[PDB]
Image 1 (cartoon, rainbow, N blue to C red):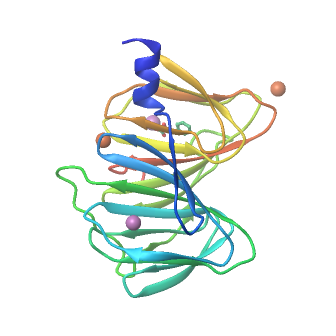
Image 2 (cartoon, rainbow, N blue to C red):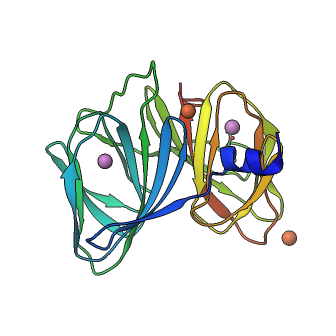
Length: 224
Ligand SMILES: O=C(O)C(=O)Cc1ccccc1
Ligand SMILES: [Co+2]
Ligand SMILES: [Co+2]
Ligand SMILES: [Fe+3]
Ligand SMILES: [Fe+3]
């Protein structure tokens, strides 16, 4: 209805969560899904836990030793992702001298079955550009597609559209305008958006440089 009301739906205001061990997170929520961007300090353990929600994790900057179930893997920035199905224990250590920036999606929606690869970690692959100039890379599982998109500056654009797939995402680069229904927000590093099925959305990068985004489809839209 109103601007504020749409903004709070589609571009929820984040809360900052701080842990005793020094991890800070920015949490944004719409209904069945939470996006959490975490800053994990050098040489820090993230204690293992487990929960009924599924969790998808990816590193955006730095390098993170991640453990899902009994699989431990080194996660490289923008080249790694895993799914921890409901109740599978997971934890991590930033074993480096550098901060780690990560994103987690935590989700529990009716009528979704949360499969994962047998060893949890997904394999990235390129495809042809989504639109010319807009390079994308994906991880895909039966119920979720993760699309990393580089939107060029100087008017790189995703035309305004809708689809039945739910689509949630986060700017992980400089910035661009994103619009959902009646609300346009200037995306910054970390800004999350949530589109329910059929809500119209599009984006335009008017800055002078490319911006990156992680865009996640429930269920897959491109690699079905
Ligand atoms: O492919 C789609 O459905 C999209 O919405 C893609 C997208 C990519 C980058 C910014 C906004 C939307
Ligand atoms: Co978790
Ligand atoms: Co879309
Ligand atoms: Fe939802
Ligand atoms: Fe320009």
